[PDB]
Image (cartoon, rainbow over all chains, first blue to last red; front, side):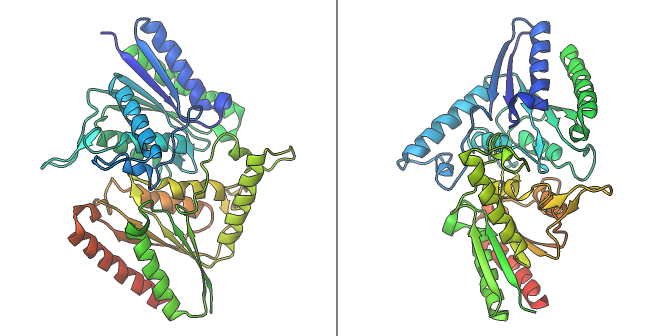
Length: 203
Length: 203
């Protein structure tokens, strides 16, 4: 029952990142319960994905016409990212909330992963995700408290995007109130870790 | 009763942009009803705002320590953007939806505009927006149909962010179903223009 785990980091705070610390904790725990499982880590901040502009979007378009140097690189990077995703069973996504949105580092990743005929396709029954049979875990950190409130659009958003490409089995792990100080940050760390333990012990 | 109008473009489709076409229509109409009003246009795609990373975020932090060359530029750009925003009465925001989110070109803009002590401040009564007395209009284009549905997080998101910095008076103009073909795109153009007319004729 061994499997492959993919971990995506999108925080811009590096070593001070609350979500990266929780991600490391996740890896450590999974490694302990499953010493045979393969674990791949991609830090979207340390290894930044380019912004999707008017030129790169052309690489995502299935065409016959020649591609510019940037488009060729964007296409190669896109294929690499998608192949990586499809090659893993458990997808861990560290998604901090910045200005009520996900980090741009993660957004750039999504913009290169979503492409017709590869991660989703059109059918007479509507869109259909091609990245299937996956189990995702989102570790979303916030400075304030938004959980189950109208100011939390990151959660429903992540759920909508992941579902669109096929990833419908998504578990959320929250770490809020970080901005209130080290006391609250520690509490959030603890609560989030317990949530990770139950997930790691459940499978 | 003359005023200044700011128009922000964030589409990556350039001349093929549905939202930029509606924005131009808006400008043309406002110019007709108010020939004395000043109109400023900033294309966030043609003149791209940098991504907020671990280094630039330091420029948004009110500190005494020396700033790196990038931080100094980011800070100068941030001040310019904020001063521009505060200098106008009517803010028109072209916000296309890409992969269920706003365009990264617009996101980068927001990440440099939101900063404590400038566009918002902390008080014993909670956060408070500093960009006040403004009237905003959002022209959001979509390939599919999400209006009033659970797949539209861009609207509540834009409303949350703009409100956070003080802009609470926001009117929305939708243009959906673009992806269904030129027939629907034209219908959306027409419907959105009527909505713009009522706004321009109302004030």
